[PDB]
Each structure stands twice: as structure tokens, then as C-alpha cells.
């Protein structure tokens, strides 16, 4: 199924008939960081499997729902269960839910993820406002836009220099200051590792030489589809470790350690993003 | 359809029956840089769609013709409408037209493209003689030769150290000097960005660290197929902008700005390449 | 055919019925470096084409056998004819033979390859104990684990920091010292070039900047599948040339020159690895 205008239009028609909500904000929450979705008001839960033309997610399993409702007086749509390219999904499968958001009226997309720290100033538990990226799959002929261009959504050759909205970064920082946790908040460049292996010790050292501040396996595909069709983006990484220190000390990361950091910061991130949604222009 | 000996042979037989031209020079012109093809003498235009085993190009649309005839007394074949890997074409689709050129008798392939400047000495409107490349798709398992080797055309493991003929670079420079535009002409290393997004500001900074002088989304796949089967190559980039300066100043590129630079240099490039064809050994 | 538990189990059942050998050591030998396999004792040769669910290898051709028997009193299984991703094999085809080794009881995998030298201390004929890697395909969305995870074999997100066992590296060095060829033996980081073109002169210079010591087109996919399912690895490169010196001097490599270096070191490598097998804990 191609992520074209006709196919996205059929999915949007179903969603509108079932939910009665017209959202102007979309959210994609990182692993272990989804508690906000369980606080959406007057909400409607829609399994992906019920939506015409949505990608099949049963091989990977686990939760996959679209959730619509209200937060802080604002109308939102959330992806509960995000799709990752290391699972084998195609370009078209990743893009179609973002283009459905566009047709539903979304103007701003808020994203969180878990990432490894490269910059020596970053420690476990820190947050990074993403200000740019290095797309290793894109340089290497695996960009999410490889294929025919879908002209109704955007141009053949997108400019990504303003993909990460500067005013949304400022608002996120302002709220952290108001609540006295600004000592946790940095800005930085995100490296997209296709995955699913964690960067090796020598890959981490290479990323440091190339000016990367953090590394993860998500986010850049959605950002590019959103920028192509004119949706503004804020993206925030939660740092689980510093891979450069780990390489110097011969220490390892694993998924268990990552999820324990997510649990330690989940409630603060939930409150932060509730206020961001409330304050959006 | 595989780019094998039998399939390329059938396409070549059709072309020979229709055109009566046996070319020893091939040309592939970059976007907005195709006016020379409209000056080919006693010419024959052959739509791709008419040629057995040529790749289907109707999803992308726009022009797709093989043009045969004479320039400066020399017999040439031109691709009018080049295939780009960011459109989703396979390795086999890109390679088959180059291998048909080989079977028709082509010994020299001349290529132009539009590119972004990385080296700080490069400005909008400059020309770069390509002397080497950095193939990000090839390091990353998307080389144009991934697949069975077609032994009739070349070896399993090609050496690319002489892919860009030094004597053709010297002849191109000599002609620029004769016409007093040598102040526009540089040499440099071409980075292959799979595309279709322009390099991000932080990707540009990374390319500078790695010794890249220019960046584009074409040319390296054709160069590798030509080198594999023993065709000599000259490749020239027209620089639309300097991406490093743009990153420092928070300024953007787009396709409209690129095509306006092409229009400004098209007539000089046309005259330059007509003389190169005339003077080839 | 997916590299899942059921499919690997059927291949292992066939092998056990035919060979009567239960191996705890596996070996994969590099090109021109396979003579040890012809010295396996009380051996059984099994063509790939006879084994249920083994990948089809007839397009590439040449030898493809599983060989079981005894070396130095130890029970081993060898791949005679290794699969390379530049031939077009999928992730699933590369992984299935390694997962069959796991089900047969393999606990240690020994690997050799031919590689180009990047580090200025490396010369033709030197050996490199691999201590880490830089996986360009993996950063670029062509990791061998992209796809559904096969949970019976390993975790969704593997940690590769101990992929190259330190004690096996020490044992290999100890034996070289005992036989007074330790002046040939280095350690270093392996860059995975997807291939099949040799790294270009400007790619070599880039690899030097990024901290790579050697470059090759194999080994990293098998290492990652082995690490995922808990098999210990020793991997050794035989250096055919120094690509940085060749770039400075405008000299070329080719497959003929590579195989001549393999012939010159084959007998020493055979004796070295026989002793390693004999001495394994
Ligand atoms: O590539 C990755 N490395 C890494 C390390 C730690 C994390 F919490 C998350 C990731 C990223 O997905
Ligand atoms: O990757 C690319 N960047 C870029 C920038 C400006 C151009 F005129 C052309 C391109 C290349 O196709
Ligand atoms: O990528 C490669 N370069 C290279 C150079 C020389 C070799 F003997 C082997 C290789 C590797 O397969």
C-alpha cells in the first residue's frame, strides 16, 4: 500500500467518522514514555488494525492504537505504539500515518525518544532538544522519501534546514526554567543509527569525530515526512547513558538499563509535555 | 529485467535497426543542462518506452529519450532524461542503458550534474572537474553492483582508482583557458548523497570534515557501471550554492534557486562540451 | 525462507542424521585460505543444495559445502564457500547457516578474511586480530538484524561491546610468539565496506580520518548473528596492501594481486589456526 493521497484520504475518513475530534496537534511518544496518552480526556482509542490502509503490525506485536481526545484544552492525536524501520517496515508504511495526521488537520508534531549520549557534557537522565540531524540511512540510499514523489503532500527535493522549529525549542526551555529543571536540558545534533544493534564502541568514537551529540534508531523518518508536508516539529531525546565513557571504561548498555532510566524520568517528561501542549501558540 | 548480456543485446539490436548511427561517445546531461541535445545533427529520437528491455519511467514522468546523431563531426548517443536512484529505480534499471552504450561501441562517457558546494573555495556558478568520489550508498550495501556479477561486461571486484580519466580533465581545463573562463574551473571530490532531501546543515559540516568538496544525488552509479566495462569518463559539476556558508548564515537552498543557476550557465556549458566532443582523441 | 527456529531446526536435523558429529567449534575461511578444511579428519561433506532451507547459491556458482569432522581432537563444522552480501543475498540467507551452527552445539566461531590496510603501520602480508568494527551498512539501515526479531535466538537490541572475545585474541597472539612470527601480528578496527568495488582513493582517506585500521566486505554480518545468539568469535584479517600508500603513489589493487598474497601466507595461517583449535579452552 503506497502512502499516496487517495489511500491516506480513506484512512482519514474512517477516523473522522469514528472519533468526532479534529486535532491540530500530533504526538509520538518514545519507549516507556507513553503515560501522557493514558491521561487524554474524552478520548477515543482506534486499533491500527481497524483503520483502512494502516500498516500491518502483527509480526512485531505489542500495542498499536491511534488515540484522539483533549489535553490542556487542545485537540490532539497520539500514536500509541510507534513504527521503527529496524523492524523491516517500508518507507510507505512509516509515512502513511504522518500523512493521515496532515489530512486530519495536524499543524504541530511533538516527539520523544530514548538515545545514547556522545557529547561529553551529557549524562544519564539528561534531556536534549534536537536542533538538527545526521541521517546515515539517507546519505546511503535508504531515505524515507526514496520512491516516487507524492506531489499533493510536498516537493520532490525538500530543504530540512528548518525541520526543528526554533520557537518550539525556546518554549520547551522556558517551561523547564519555570519549574527549575533547566540544569537537565541541553541542545544537540541527533545521529540516526538504523539499528537494531546499539552503536559499537568504535562507532561511538566515530560519531564523536563527526559532530554528533546523541544517537538513536527513530525520529528522523517521521521528521522528514512531517517537514515535507509542512508540519512543525519539536523532538526531545532522553539520554540513557554516555557511550563514549562506556567505551573508555569497557562497560555495556542493554534494553533493561534503558527502560529503568525511562521509568525514572517518565513523570517529569509527562508534566513537561502537558504544559508544552497547553502553551503552544 | 536484469542488466545482462542477452537483454542489453536485444535493446542494442533495435537501436541499430532504427538509427543507422554507430556512436563512440555517450553523454548524460544534468538538470537544466540539456540544450546541447537539441543541436545534435541528422539526429534520431527514440523514446525509452519503445526500446526492448529499457526501464519503465512513467511513474516519475517527464522526458525519456535516447538521441543519436553527430556533434562536431563525431558520432554520439545522448540520454535525454536521466534516471536517478532516489526515484526508486533498481541497480539493474540504472545499469542497463550504460551497458547498451557499451554494446553500441561507446568508448567515452561525458557527464554533467548540479551539486552543492562544500569546499570553502567554491561559489555559486563555479564548475568542478570531478577527480574522485565518496560513495555513501556503496559503503552502506547499496552499491550499484550489488547482485550477481555479469561477467561479459567486467570483473567481480572493480578498481575505481582511474575511473575519472586524467587526460580528459586536462583537455577540459585547456579549453576553458583558451576561452578565458578558467577562473571558474576547480577540481574536487564528489560525495554521493542518495537523496532526495538536500544535505542538512549538520550533514554539510560532516562532509567538510571528511574531505568532500561537492555533494550530489547522481553520477556515481553511472560512473561505476562505465568503469566496470572499460568506458572512460569525464564528469563536471555546476555548483548552485555553498552549503557550509548557508549553514553559518541560516539560509536555505531549494529547487527553484538551483534551476536559476543552471539557466545562467547553460549556454557556456553547451559551448564548452561541444568543443570537448570535437577535440576528443 | 526466514532464519527462524523452525527452519533452522529442520536443517540441523538433516545434518545430524547424515554426519554423526556434534561440533562445538565452527569455522569460516576467507578467500584462498581454505586449505585447513581439506585436512579435517573422518570428515563428511554436505552440499548446501542438499540441506533443507539452506540458501540457493547457484547464481553465484562455485563451491558451497558444509564439512564436519575432527581437528586436533576437537569436533568442528566448516563453511566451505562463504556467502557475501555484495552477491545480493538477504539478511535471512546470511543468518540461517550461523543459527544452524548454534542448534548443532557450536560455542566458538573462528573467522578469517582478506582486507585492505588503512593504518600506516600495516603492510602486505601482515595479520590483524579484529578487536572492534565500524558497520557502515548497519548505520545506514542495512544491518543483518533488520526485520522481525527471532526471540528464540537472542534479544531485540544486542550489545556488541564484547563481540570479539579478548581471551581468544590473547591465545592467538601467544601461539604466534611461540612460533616467532609475532612481528606479523597487529590488532585493529575493521570497517565493513558493503562492496563489491574496492574502496576508492578518497574513501580510503576518509576511513583513515574515522579511525579504521582495515577494510573488507565480509565478517561483520556473521559476527553480529553469532553475538546475538551467544557464540564467541575470533576474527583475523590478512592484509593484501596499504590503500593509503597506494593512494599517495597512484597505484592500484586488483583480485589477482589479492589472491597472490593469500597464496603466500596460506600455509602459515593453516598451521596457526590448527593450533588455535587444539588449544581452545
Ligand atoms: O542507537 C541507539 N543507541 C542507544 C543507546 C541508548 C539508548 F537508550 C538508545 C539508543 C539508540 O536507539
Ligand atoms: O545532494 C545535493 N545537494 C545539492 C545542493 C544543490 C544542488 F544544486 C544540488 C544538490 C545535490 O543533488
Ligand atoms: O573492501 C575491501 N578492500 C580490500 C582491499 C584488499 C583486499 F585484499 C580486500 C579488500 C576488502 O574486501
Image (cartoon, coloured by chain):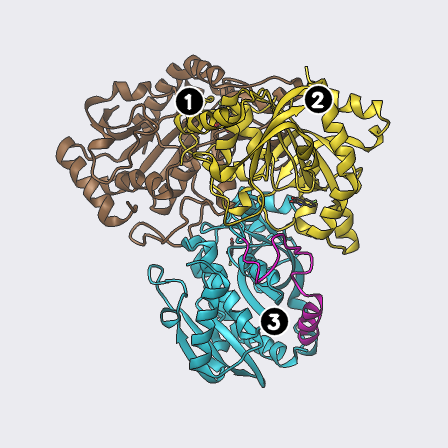
Chain colours: A yellow, B brown, C cyan
Magenta stretch: includes residue C167: yes
Identity of the residue drawn at 53% across and 49% down: A60
Tell me where residue C129 appears, x and y as whole percent.
Answer: 64, 64
Using the numbered discs, state the Cα–Cα distance from disc 2 to disc 3 in whole angstroms.
57 Å
Q: Which element is circle 1 on?
A: loop
Q: Are marks 2 and 3 in contact (CB under 8 Å)?
A: no
Q: CA distance from mark 1 to mark 3?
A: 53 Å
Chain containing mark 2 = A
Q: In terms of image quadrants, where is residue A170? A: top right
Residue drawn 46% across the image and 15% down it: B256
- Foreground: A53 or A4? A53
Q: Is disc 2 in the same subunit as disc 1? A: yes
Both marks 1 and 3 on one chain: no
Q: Is residue B158 magenta?
A: no
Residue C108 is labelled as 3
Please state the horizontal and vertical placement of residue B266, each as a whole percent of the image.
Answer: 39, 16
Q: Is residue C192 left or right of residue B112?
A: right
Distance Cα–Cα, label 2 vs label 1: 35 Å
Where is mark 1, residue-wise?
Answer: A151
Whole-percent x, y for residue A25 in the image: 61, 23
Q: Are marks 2 and 3 on the same chain?
A: no
| Magenta residues (range) | C149-176
Amino acid at each position: 500500500v503506497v502512502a499516496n493521497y487517495e489511500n491516506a484520504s480513506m484512512a482519514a475518513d474512517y477516523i473522522k467518522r469514528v472519533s468526532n475530534v479534529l486535532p491540530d496537534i500530533g504526538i509520538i511518544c518514545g519507549s516507556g514514555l507513553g503515560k501522557l496518552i493514558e491521561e487524554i480526556e474524552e478520548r477515543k482509542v482506534i486499533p491500527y488494525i481497524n483503520i483502512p490502509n494502516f500498516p500491518k503490525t502483527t509480526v512485531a506485536g505489542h500495542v498499536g492504537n491511534l488515540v484522539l481526545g483533549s489535553v490542556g484544552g487542545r485537540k490532539i492525536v497520539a500514536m500509541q505504539g510507534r513504527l521503527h524501520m529496524y523492524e523491516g517496515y517500508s518507507n510507505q508504511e512509516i509515512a502513511l500515518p504522518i500523512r493521515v495526521m496532515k489530512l486530519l488537520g495536524v499543524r504541530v508534531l511533538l516527539i520523544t525518544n530514548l538515545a545514547g549520549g556522545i557529547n561529553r557534557k551529557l549524562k544519564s537522565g539528561d534531556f536534549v532538544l534536537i536542533k538538527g540531524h545526521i541521517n546515515f540511512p539517507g546519505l546511503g540510499l535508504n531515505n524515507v522519501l526514496v520512491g516516487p514523489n507524492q506531489d499533493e503532500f510536498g516537493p520532490r527535493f525538500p530543504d530540512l534546514s528548518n525541520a526543528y522549529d526554533r520557537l518550539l525549542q525556546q518554549l520547551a526551555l522556558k517551561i523547564a526554567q519555570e519549574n527549575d529543571f533547566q540544569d537537565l536540558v541541553h541542545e544537540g545534533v541527533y545521529a540516526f543509527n538504523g539499528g537494531p544493534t546499539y552503536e559499537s564502541p568504535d562507532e561511538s568514537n566515530m560519531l564523536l569525530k563527526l559532530g554528533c551529540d546523541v544517537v538513536g534508531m527513530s525520529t528522523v523518518p517521521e521528521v522528514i515526512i512531517a517537514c515535507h508536508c509542512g508540519i512543525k516539529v519539536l523532538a526531545v531525546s532522553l539520554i540513557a547513558n554516555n557511550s563514549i565513557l562506556d567505551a573508555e571504561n569497557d562497560v555495556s548498555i542493554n534494553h533493561e538499563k534503558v527502560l529503568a532510566v525511562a521509568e525514572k524520568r517518565a513523570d517529569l517528561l509527562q508534566m513537561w509535555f502537558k504544559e508544552i501542549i497547553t502553551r503552544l501558540p
